[PDB]
Structure formats: C-alpha cells, structure tokens
Length: 168
Length: 168
Length: 88
Length: 88
Image (cartoon, rainbow over all chains, first blue to last red; front, top):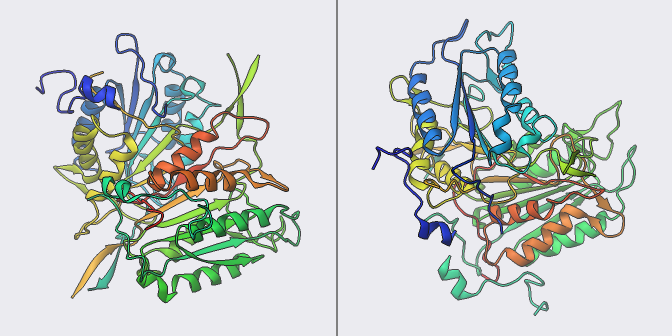
C-alpha cells in the first residue's frame, strides 16, 4: 500500500533483508536522524525559467522521505548561497545519529558546473562538483565519516547533443 | 595450475558461467582479437626515476594476457607521444573483432593529470583523463562502440597525504 | 589517542549526462533523469544496492532518440554496498 | 540508414587515489594500487564483475597507515555488468 511512509517505494521484506561483511551498516529506525538536502534553481536572472522543476522537487522530496530522510529544500540560490547552505548542512548535529545522506542539485549547468541564479556569460555564477565533495568530506564534515554520501546532479554539462551517427 | 595461459588468474568454471540480460556479451575465444595498451613512464627529464615501474609493467602485462588481451607496452613518452599512441590504438583493426579493451597509464601525476617524460613546473607536459576518454569514445573510436573500455591510472593527483585526524 | 582517516571516502556522484553534453527536462513532466531515477529507486531499492540501481538507470537510457543523454557515476569511493533497506 | 549512438558509453576509469592526493609506489615491490588490483583481479575475475572487483580493491585500502590512499572509480558509463569470464 502507498498510504504508508514509504509511499510508492517497494518494500524490502525480512526474508530479503537476511538474504542480503561488505554492506554499509544501517542505524536503528527508532533513533536515527537521516538528513537530505535538495537545492533547486528554477528562477534565473539571465537564463530561461526551468519549467517543470516543481515536478522534480515533489518527486525527489517524497522519494527521499520514503527512504527515511528528512528533506531540506532550498530554491533559487547563487553559487555563494549554495556554498553557505552546504556548509550549514555539513554542520548539522543530526548527521552524528545518521548512517548516510543524499544531496540533490537541480539547475542549469555548463561544462564547469552548476549555475547559480545570477549566472550569465559575462559574470559566471558556478558551483563546481569538486567544491561539493570538499564541503562534505571527512575534513569539513567529520559527522559523515564512513557514511554513504550520494550526490545527484540534474544539469547540462555542455551544449553538445551527446550523440554520433553510425550506419548498420 | 599456473602453467596455462591464464597463469595465476582463478578460472571461471562452466557451472559458474551459466549461473552468471544485463551482462556485456563475450566474443568467441577462437576468433576474438582482444587488445590492451600499457603506457608507463619510468625515466624522466626533470622528475625522479620511478623505481619499481618494471614490476608494475610485468604484473599488468601478464595479468591482461591471462585475461585474453594482446598487450602493447609503450615506455617513456611525452603527453604528445601518448596522444599519438592512443590515436593509433583507437584505429587498430583488431578492435572490430574484440569485445572490450583495457588501457593502463603509469607515471608521475599532478592534479591536472598524467606527467609526460619532459614534464617540469616551468614547462608542463600533462595528459588529461578527459583527453583519454575523448580519444576512445564513439566519435574517435567507433570500433569500440558498446564495448567496455577499462582505464587504469597509477599516478599522484596532487601533493596531499589524503588523510585527516580524528579522536575515538 | 588520534587516528588517521581518508579525507575522501564513501562518496558516489550520479550526473544526468556525460561531460560536454545536454540533459533534458520536460516542461510539464519534469527532468527525464530525475523521473527515471525515482522510478528505478522505487522499484529496485528493496533488492539492489545504489551502484546497481544507478547502472540500471544508465541501461534505461541506452537507446538514443531525438533527445538523448547518458547518466554517469563519478568519483566513487564507496567501499561497501549501499543498500537502502526500505521499510527498515 | 544511419542511427544515433551515445558519444560516451561503456567506460570505467579506476584511479590510484582521490583528487589532490598521493599514490604510493614501493621501489622494489612496485605500485601498491597496481599490486592490489592484480591480486583482486586474479582472485575475483571468476566470480565478480569489474565494478564489484574495483569496490573490493577500495575496501582493501580502508584502514589508513603511514602511506594512505583511496582508489576511486570515475566517469562510469557501463550499462551492463562486465564479467571477464576467465578461461572462456
């Protein structure tokens, strides 16, 4: 049934759980405080409006909640604001009593990285993937040491169609 | 026995093979022409000699042969020579009757990429991972379309020890 | 006493397309990668680890149409299998 | 007739360390990553796909000593499991 907390996520039965040394440990459901962050840029100063972004926010938010995460949603941020939000996320006390995290970034993007709300060709406003990793590593986020950190990025990485032709 | 062509590589039995829709197809052993390339820089103009590189060459060469690949070994090349060798490798007719490939790069390295034999701080001689992918993609190497391309890189990616301290 | 830990470990990134290349977004249906990822997570989180799930997402994009893209996993330092164990 | 294909697909890179960080090489015993990779390939090629093998290599580096490094898989566009099927 989809009426439960896991919604439309298919359940792992107890028989399947015992069937599955090389697995990340899961914290007790009763006491764990899983955290997730979604940053989505829909409204921009110079680049077109990302119509349909609300559908992505809804889907990802509900999915991560279904998987047991408390989801923070931040919208329409500059690269600098994204950095500030990431640093704040990395400092959250809940990570200490968490076993993992998800980070979701959804925006316009170029080869270099993810576009902030104020991005243009003259004045670039870019957040690099390298910066995301650095802010979440053991040095800057010790609370997530040994814990899975899943980073999801919806964005272009350039202008190319990503295809080549071939004849059969 | 290690006297066979597979040497010290543990064999996959016929019972294990049948036990294993989502797997890359393997070409007939009798007719396939698998190719592999090892580029190893040991002797440099400005950076120290990579003592023990010969051990790596021996091990990787024999392993890839054990797995069924014909191994080309190229030593002490500039980034430009590496590029030329990669382009030549991508054009090899054997790839057409091959099901996969391995590329192995072993040298000194910095953050930007892999050092050629003539590398120094004043005059950089670097091959980027991005260039390796580009030279082996569907556009520049159509013979390896749909086929696994495994790239192995032994090199530093910077000067940092890669560690942080924590107290238990 | 103090101990050493790897500075970067237990990461996995999953990007909507490959370097240089576009990712597609339907104006009413949303981003195709995001939609595809949700569908695969819903279906396979119970039985597969995240690396296996992301691989299945990549397979689902295999046949290119007019709006093609290939999702990619990057900078993976997962040392174990990450099972979500939904329901637990 | 012509057909479209993804420009970048079926790649996997495996690097000896993470960005910014050193990789170690013993002067007589060789590169630790290379040696470790060979050992794991020899043992696990029969039973595991390459992504599983590379994960095991990463696990083997988990406990850091005086000369630490964490191998990483990058730019993965494998859409299927790559089994080497040694002997076949």
